[PDB]
């Protein structure tokens, strides 16, 4: 498995969703399975997906150990750095686990 911080970017408007994962590939697969079931945690990402389906690109921002202290700090760094709340799909600061 490969862990760390990642971004899910809408290729139509460049807006992003910043998250953390124990394993990138599996976390991304879970995001889209959730969006298809219509019960994703982010109403903003869900709305975009309902309108466009999977027009997103997933990429790694930082590969780092999946440890709470490190993950929350780095996830929040990227959320702010990429302004993913005001201009993205994140609905709040980072969570872990």
Image (cartoon, rainbow, N blue to C red):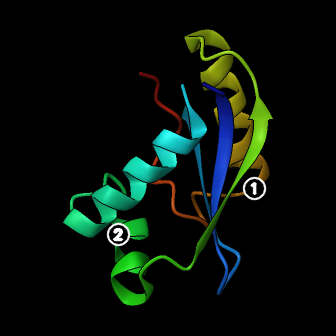
Residue at image coords 72%, 28%: 74
- Considering the numbered disc 2 on the image, is that residue within a helix, a strand or a loop? helix
Label located before the other in sequence (1 or 2): 2
Residue 21 position (above or below residue 60): above
Q: Nearer the viewer, residue 2 or 90?
A: 2
Left or right of 7 in this view: 91? left
Q: Is residue 87 visible?
A: no
Q: Position of residue 11 (x, y in %)?
A: 67, 80
**Mark count:** 2
The residue tagged 2 is: 46
- Considering the numbered disc 1 on the image, is that residue within a helix, a strand or a loop? loop
Left or right of 4 in this view: 30? left
The disc placed on residue 82 is 1
Q: Nearer the viewer, residue 75 or 24?
A: 24
Q: Position of residue 10 (x, y in %)?
A: 61, 75
Picture quadrant where residue 22 is located:
top right
Q: Is residue 50 visible?
A: yes
Front tag of 1 and 2:
2
Residue at image coords 60%, 11%: 67
Tell me the quadrant of the picture where the N terminus can be found.
top right
Q: Are marks 1 and 2 in contact (CB under 8 Å)?
A: no
Q: Position of residue 21 (x, y in %)?
A: 55, 32
Residue at image coords 40%, 77%: 49
Residue 49 position (above or below residue 20): below
Mark 2 neighbour density, 10 Å: few (under 14) some (14–19) many (20 or more):
many
Q: Position of residue 73 (x, y in %)?
A: 68, 23
Mark 1 neighbour density, 10 Å: few (under 14) some (14–19) many (20 or more):
some
Picture quadrant where residue 19 is located:
top right
| Marks 1/2: CA–CA distance | 19 Å
Left or right of 41 in this view: 96? right
Tell me the quadrant of the picture where the C terminus can be found.
top left
């Amino acid at each position: 498995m490969k862990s760390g911080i990642y971004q899910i970017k809408n290729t139509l408007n460049n807006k992003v969703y910043v998250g953390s994962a124990k394993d990138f590939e599996k976390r991304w697969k879970r995001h889209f399975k959730d969006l298809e079931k219509g019960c994703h945690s982010s109403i903003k990402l869900q709305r975009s997906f309902n309108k466009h389906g999977n027009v997103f690109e997933c990429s790694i921002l930082e590969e780092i150990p999946y440890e709470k202290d490190l993950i929350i700090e780095r996830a929040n760094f990227w959320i702010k750095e990429l302004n993913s709340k005001i201009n993205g799909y994140n609905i709040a600061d980072a969570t872990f686990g």
